[PDB]
Structures are given as C-alpha cells and as structure tokens.
Length: 426
DNA sequence: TTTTTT
Ligand SMILES: Nc1ncnc2c1ncn2[C@@H]1O[C@H](COP(=O)(O)OP(=O)(O)O)[C@@H](O)[C@H]1O
Ligand code: ALF
Ligand SMILES: [Mg+2]
Image (cartoon, rainbow, N blue to C red; front, top):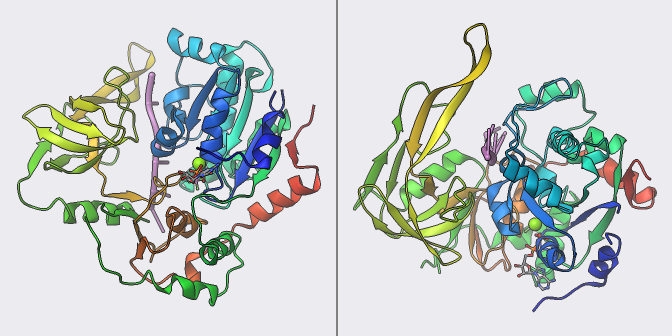
C-alpha cells in the first residue's frame, strides 16, 4: 500500500527518450518508486547497483556482475578485458531501459565502461547504444570508493570523481528531479536534524537531540544490526557475537598462487547454528545472489543449510575463485589461471560496513562512527532507522564526523540553474 | 580507511 507523491507522477511521463537522474533525501522513496516503474514501464528493464546489498534491495545484480567489469579503473586507452557470452548479449539487446540505484557510489569510468560495452554490442555510436537509462541515488550520501592510486590514473581523463564526470555526458545528458517526501522516518524533530547533517548546515544545538544514542541498553533479542566504518570493527563484532563455543570452522583450500591480499572470501569461516550470514557470490541455479542475508540452520561436513531473509532454504556448496593473471606463453601474452581458492560463499553478517548498508531500512541499528572518513558516511549510517528510539551509538555524534564535498554544491548549482538538466541536450 | 566481474 504505497503513496505516489505528485513528483513521482511528474517523473513517469518524462520517460515515455531522454535519460533522467532521480535524487532525494535518504528514505524519500527512490528505491521503492524504482521498483514500481519496472511494472508501469512497458519496457524491458534490467536492474543493477554498485554494491550487492543495494542491488538485492533493488531487484538486480552488481554492476560488475552485469557488465563483466574488472575491479581496476578503465581509461579510454585501456582495452576491454572481457567478452560477453551470447546469453548476456540476449539480455542486453532485449533490454529497453537500464536502471542504476545508489548511483552516487559509481565511479565515472564505470559508466564509460558501460557506455563502451553497450555501444559495442548494439554496434552503434549512440551513447550507451541508444538505451534509455534512469539513475537513482543521492550525491550527499556516499561517494564511490576509489583508492588514490586509482584516482590519479583517472585525473588524467576526468575533471572529477563522481558519476556525472563520466565522459559520455559530453555526448548525452539527463534530467534531474528531487523527490521531497521523506517516508522512512516520521518524527520531524528527528528529520530536521538529518536534513541538516546532510547539507552540512547543522548546529550543535540540533546535535543535542542525538544525545540519547550514547550508551543505551541492548534490548536483544528482534535483534540489532551493527553498521561500522571499518571492516576491522565488522570482523570483531561478529566474532564477539557467535562466540567461541559450539563452533564449526571451515578452512579455505588454495590450489597454487593466490595472495591473502585479494582472497575474496573467508579464510577460516567459523559458524554456529543461528549465525547471521551474507552470501558473497551469485548462483542462479540455487538462486542466491551476493547481498542476500540468511539464518544458518544445518551444518554438515560439506553443505551449509541456511534460510534466507526472503524465505527459501538454500543448501550452500563451496565455491571456487580463480586467480587469473597475465603471462607469457609460446610468445603469446595470455591470462592463465595461476591459482584458486575454495570456501563456502558465506560470511558473518551481524555487522556490515556503513557502505554495504546504504539503501537499506531498519528498526533497530547499532552504529560505530567514532572514526568516519567519507562524506555523508555518518548521514547514511544514522538515516537507516525509522525512529531514533531504535538507534545506538558507539560515541557521541560530533561535527567532526561531517565532511563536506563542495564538488556537490557546484553540481546542484549547474543543473538547478539550467532547467534541471545536465550534459549535452538533444 | 571504503567496493567491485563473466
Ligand atoms: N511512497 C512511499 N509511501 C510510503 N512509504 C514509503 C514510500 N517509499 C518508501 N517508504 C518507506 O520508506 C522505506 C525506505 O524507502 P526507500 O525507497 O528505501 O528510500 P530511498 O529512496 O532512500 O531508497 C520503505 O521501506 C518504506 O517503509
Ligand atoms: F538511498 Al536509500 F535507503 F535507498 F537512503
Ligand atoms: Mg535506494
């Protein structure tokens, strides 16, 4: 039983073939309105998002899954690493509209990599292969994570590190609408404080509403979720729950060469009945995708049985990761698998990073924000909850947790003064 | 520091 704000009506006919970027405060109804348009579109829509949890929340898959995109940045001079199977092309030409939720965490070059890969399959110079595309997200929440060495690599090509700095907006553009009804939260004394943490204009008197969060009793269990700034805090929290007793350890097996730096899974996956888990890969067959959460019910020597948040029981077998590297063969340069690891594609999920929690909704969260470092990271971390009564904090909410990004004010200025559009018009 | 492939 959902409301359609007057703004939501204003969008829809704009699409029936210009592109559109829809933004608005945390819990303004972006991710739900998105779900509703996939029905009322008449177009074959394919849904993807930068991270698996947000993707699961929106219906679809990660952007790297969808477009077979390797991890590192991709320049105009870099060669496309991966080719598409004939299924994934079927998926992409049959696609009429592409969606992207939590667009704010998407690097500029991802879009250009998606641009190039789509122009290639549609055999056209149309931007994106002439595929209408609509973007959901919010710039004043989390930006894309990049690692500085990656950043200078793209400073050679990009005047900025946000999704709108994609070079294909030199060949096309999008409209911009701001949904303005915050649904998820109801107390305005609350709501007013986050809108201000969002736009960097909050005062230490409004921050004194958030005094209650410091040091409240754990009413569990209905149990709490822990969302953190760093994985260090994540791994400790879940080891703290779960505990040392009644445990089953499952060790990774690693064929040859695969450095512990980039093993994408748990080395020693320790679990007990009733442990809260997340799945890390996609298996269409069984139906698990990377982001879904479950509850573990049956641990045998080689199969882990877990019942998902959606309801269906899965039997997890182990999954194998391959370390493909580039090497020299009979005077040929070729990606040869130099190793492999094999664990169950599961990890503990009583605690997740604030990054993985963007897009989600909760009734009782626990936040660990004493060491924030990204703009809008605090803002995401405490806008997840419907009510304040339901949030705990590891430290007081100080203004040192708010980090403004002035690239974002300029971007609003640019589009708000030019009729809510951005990029080349046609 | 934070995420992410077929
Ligand atoms: N149109 C709506 N009418 C009523 N409640 C809504 C609406 N949209 C969202 N909500 C409530 O807010 C929650 C989160 O909204 P969501 O769409 O996830 O926000 P975001 O735009 O930040 O993704 C939903 O789970 C629902 O409880
Ligand atoms: F952008 Al959201 F919950 F999807 F804040
Ligand atoms: Mg969303």
